[PDB]
Image (cartoon, coloured by chain):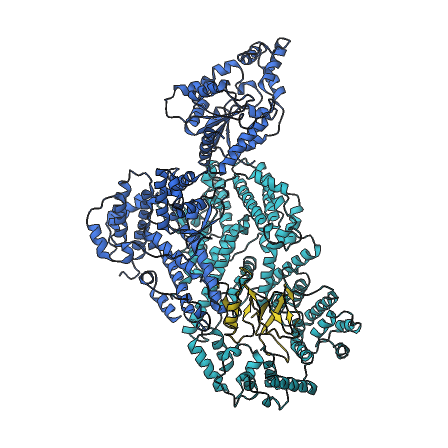
Chain colours: A cyan, B blue, C yellow
Amino acid sequence: YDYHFEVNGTVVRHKNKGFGYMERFFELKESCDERSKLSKKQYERFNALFNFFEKNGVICMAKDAGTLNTSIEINSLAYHGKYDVMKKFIEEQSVSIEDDYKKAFFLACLGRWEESYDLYSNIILNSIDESNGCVYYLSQINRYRIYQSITQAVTQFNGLGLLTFGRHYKPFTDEFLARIEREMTNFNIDDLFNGMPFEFQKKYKILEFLSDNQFLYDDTVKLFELTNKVRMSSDIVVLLRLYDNLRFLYENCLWSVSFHEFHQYIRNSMSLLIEKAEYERTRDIDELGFSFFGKKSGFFMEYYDFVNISRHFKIDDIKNLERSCSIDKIRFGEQEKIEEYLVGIAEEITKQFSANGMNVVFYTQFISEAKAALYFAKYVKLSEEGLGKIVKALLFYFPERDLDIGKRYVWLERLTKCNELPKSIISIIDDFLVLQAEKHIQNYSEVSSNGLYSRDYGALIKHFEKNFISKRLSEITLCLTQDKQKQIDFLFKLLPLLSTNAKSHLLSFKNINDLMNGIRIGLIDEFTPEHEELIIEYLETRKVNYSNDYMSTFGIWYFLEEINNSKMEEFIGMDDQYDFFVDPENFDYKKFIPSWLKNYNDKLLGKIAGNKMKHHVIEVLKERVKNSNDKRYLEILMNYFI
Amino acid sequence: LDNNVVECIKEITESSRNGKLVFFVGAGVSTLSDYPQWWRLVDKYHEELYGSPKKGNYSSDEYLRIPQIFYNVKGEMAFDGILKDFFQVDKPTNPIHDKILAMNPAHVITTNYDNLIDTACRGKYFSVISAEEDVANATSSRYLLKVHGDFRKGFKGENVVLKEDDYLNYDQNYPLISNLMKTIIATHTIVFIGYGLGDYNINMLLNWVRKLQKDSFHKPFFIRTDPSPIENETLIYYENKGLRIIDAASLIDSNEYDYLERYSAVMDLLIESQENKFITKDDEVIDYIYGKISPLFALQYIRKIDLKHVFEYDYHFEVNGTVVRHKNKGFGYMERFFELKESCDERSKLSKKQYERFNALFNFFEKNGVICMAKDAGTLNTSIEINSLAYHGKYDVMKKFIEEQSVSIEDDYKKAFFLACLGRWEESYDLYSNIILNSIDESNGCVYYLSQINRYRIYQSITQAVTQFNGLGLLHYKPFTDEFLARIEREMTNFNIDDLFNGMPFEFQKKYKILEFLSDNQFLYDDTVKLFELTNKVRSEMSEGSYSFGMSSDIVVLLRLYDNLRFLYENCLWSVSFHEFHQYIRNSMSLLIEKAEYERTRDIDELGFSFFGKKSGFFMEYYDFVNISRHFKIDDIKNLERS
Amino acid sequence: ATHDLVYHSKINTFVWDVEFDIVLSDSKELNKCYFVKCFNPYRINGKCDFAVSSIDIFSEGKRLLIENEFNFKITKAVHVATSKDVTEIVLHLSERISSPFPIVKEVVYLD
């Protein structure tokens, strides 16, 4: 406690009551005439200390401050996820014990926990001499952590989640589990530091907290400051402390980076930082000026922040970040390095799927990062080649058991929002849907969770490319027969993409139920007079009959100016919805209630917004908002009716 | 099993958990690894000296007389050559070595001259002492005391006690090692292994322990592994001489030529019983619960969460008052205790002292609000009540309470807290010093620790106030005696707060385990992480517009809040002074107010479920109001008014 | 126990832990089945465009093809987790709302 070392790279005297050795040292390093008064051994010791302080980013006192660069960089290969480099470095022969330690950490990071444990045991056995316990000690810690992880995996893997092939293959054998339990039957880590030689305890006092089960309590507690609503900056100090912690944990090859506590700390820090930035921006724009502040948030985030977000965030946390602190108004950083990261992770997932030699633990530890990365890749401008590679990896080589058709449709649609659709990805999507048609050949059925299917893809293509024609589907459907029905069903589900000849050919392959089924998916897009006559007959049958909601769709259809018939005025008398959708001028609005208002889509609400019953709906929305502060009612009022 | 054996096992386990176990490893353990015994060398010397062997004339003294004759006749080089020839082999370690190391002994004293017990430590660091100069360069605080001169320095015969003359001049040759052995034996708890009941070393040690006073030693344990079950008279005589004997025989039984199985059975029994707590009927359950609870009686109130630390993660404790089995494999004392609490009839099956201790435990659990388990939990109602005068804010009350003389040290501690919250920090420091000085007497020491922490806290408070509040708007009062500002400096200079708890009696570190968290910000992290997570969840429900018709999550937050405040105020602690606590309280209350405001308005509640019932509702009382007025700033109040 | 019940705002629906033994029209009796609703207001639909939320019905966890949507024959509701005939409340609540389907297992927010 002699000196306070502020995170920005400065020092200050705090409780030094003796000679100011820090000031003398920094004066000696500042000038050249200060040197040459010291012996050769002192000269080389000062040179080594200067090099160490340069590598550690310590500059000078706060009096001689001004424009501190504070540029961070981490040169640990495992951080950047260059897995091929770790794979090639593992097989290479190791020279010294430090290379063995780094190899053990790399093996642990790759899911080969067996070899990591054996290597740690061998390292502990070999090196016990000298005051280099700084390796030995750390080795023990890593080993213990690995063991903990191993047992946790077991009690999480063989206990639940039988969806994996077999009984999860039992990734670790039972004999090794018994040996693990035998070697660590009563190992206590809290007394590891005390038993080591007293000179080690004197020198390496700073490494004590590693043996504790919790060591991020101080930063997590200090995170409270960002919630201060009152009017260096605390964002700078918090972010720099986070970078310091990440650099220390990753550069020294410590396994404690793979625990839940660190992930929770990372998520809390990032979420609080983004919340503070957005709150400050919104308060400034509300108070200072509508566009004087520029309406752009000052929190720039870069490659390091993106990789941290990808690594340590789950899906729902990113969902919270986007719905509360929307990032579309946040500007990115260097897009090129982000593109390199994305192409690397896509290459990794492609290799993992293709080689078929998957490892369950690495599977679980990596696809979380993968899904986070692809989900967050929406906000980055990406070149055509990177887009093609990412789509190729995601559409085909992403395993079914984690990503289904519906969520893959989410990812792809979310990816191009700002990336557009050059010819390449339309070609690759056409290839994917052609392959899907091939696999439809039967006891086969697509599974989705969000109720979406492959047809959406074609619609999206038709949304972006109206004139595109898929020839391969035409070739498939020319040879198509009627023995197998599911394939032609998929063919009508992809009707617009086909050519006129294919459409005419399939038209030969197909009461009010038939018309309703065709119109639900939209095969008979037009309204032929025969269909209108069937409509009249069904309405007359209902009227002479006089409750599922099937006829209100017909009033909606007439409201869409798609039914050119004058007999809809004579079939009213039961439902207020039909009268409103056919004769709104004479309609009684006492029976009108806004429950159906939350069911129409953009086109219907836009059409009804400009139609002139507008005062009736405006007063209905007024009263509904007054009695209850429903988000949907106020939102629809603002976006459509104002 | 025999009751005395159970008692010995319990004492050995208790000593092992406290790091006060020392193993006296004999020569039979090294024999199990097929190490060449001494009698082989004796016979070889007999052969090389005379020319023929004879087993019949091999008494106890011959084992030392024959090598001495060989050394005195043939010389020294022949002795070293024979020793090198017969002791250069290397042998694998024993499972018994791993079993003894797995008990975590503080020191290991061995009379062997082998390397097996060393090469067995696997990843354990021991400072090996086998000579005279090695006791001065002890690099660590854990001793592997090879009493009889290991062969590390070489295979010469002058480095090990084998012949008779060396045994005669042992005290004159090895004073330091003998003194160290006797000190270790007097301090820690000794467990012998691999020794014959008639061996020379045991007899010498008994002769030495005879000279000691009748009391003032811990009777060493002797684990005997011999084919013949021991006799009653020999056992009683050796117990009278000062040993407690546990015999491997009469427990497992085997043939005459097998030795590994008996050692294995004894060590497996010890290791298995280490984690197990010997609980059979209700009396043991209540005794153990009282033993692990009673030190907490000094504090007025403790929060429910850190209870999970007292029981060593044996039972997850929820804020609402329910408990859930987490890492318990034994009798399940919580289940039986709850059954005893529910059923009045079974309370008559306990002895009077156990009945009184159970009554005290039940009262303590009722004050803490622990209700029952999760399955038996129905409609649980929790009241909020704090008995701190300073919390309510009737300053005349503790003014006229500090006016007069107190009656006990705890009363003085209350006076110190009241003075600290009354602004007279000088008198607060003076009376805290008076307390820590008037406390030379204590059966617990908790008051001493708490007073030291509070004194350091108020010291930092006055230092920060003096240093910062000088140009903040003061312009000068900063009123304190000039000598006082240097007295606090020189006095509270070397006093480090991180190592405070590490320097307290070994039982205090075992009983008041939770209080360590008071020395730092630790006592907030475990709760603030949950607060952040629940904040995120509640805001997600806020954004999606979902309405919950069951029980809301916010109650959990609320409970934690109140508990924290009570634990900080009923114990009269100055830690409520910092701004971290204020920020935490402010965040929790902002969350609660926002959630209540959102739950105030609904759409379908009236039409529909309203007939079934109505649980929704939120209310500010006295407590909420005082907390708002104390732990909030004006701008945040304006912000929440706007929101 | 109505803890499961979660009521939404943008769709005005219920989410329970129950299961339905629906009977289809024309005396077509069905086994246990359940509903799943997915809300998507940004769908770029075609000429047939009225609904924002897609409702799907699955029997035994398998997608059941829908041709005649005439399942106005009530059901016997069983609270899948605790297995209780919540059916009476099921009607109590379905007769009190205008939504065609009052209870779904969960609502998927694609928006």
Q: Nearer the viewer, residue B579 or C38?
A: C38
User: B231 above or below B5?
Assistant: above
Q: Quadrant of residue A447?
A: bottom right
Q: Quadrant of residue A482?
A: bottom right
Count the numbered circles shown: 0
User: A391 above or below A204?
Assistant: below
Q: Quadrant of residue B440?
A: top left
Residue A574 location in percent, x, y? 55, 84
Residue B476 location in percent, x, y? 25, 58
User: C2 above or below B7?
Assistant: below
Q: Is residue A616 left or right of residue B370?
A: right
Q: Is residue A190 left or right of residue A165?
A: left
Residue B307 location in percent, x, y? 41, 48
User: A414 above or below A209?
Assistant: below
Which residue reaches farthest right? A479
Q: Nearer the viewer, residue C33 or A351?
A: C33
Q: Nearer the viewer, residue B610 or A170?
A: B610
Q: Nearer the viewer, residue B281 or A150?
A: B281
Q: Which residue does the image show at 44% across and 80% down from the upper left?
A: A623
Residue A24 location in percent, x, y? 41, 47
Q: Which residue does the image show at 55% across and 21% down from the upper left?
A: B228
Please say whether residue B118 is visible from this viewpoint. no
Please say whether residue A450 is visible from this viewpoint. yes
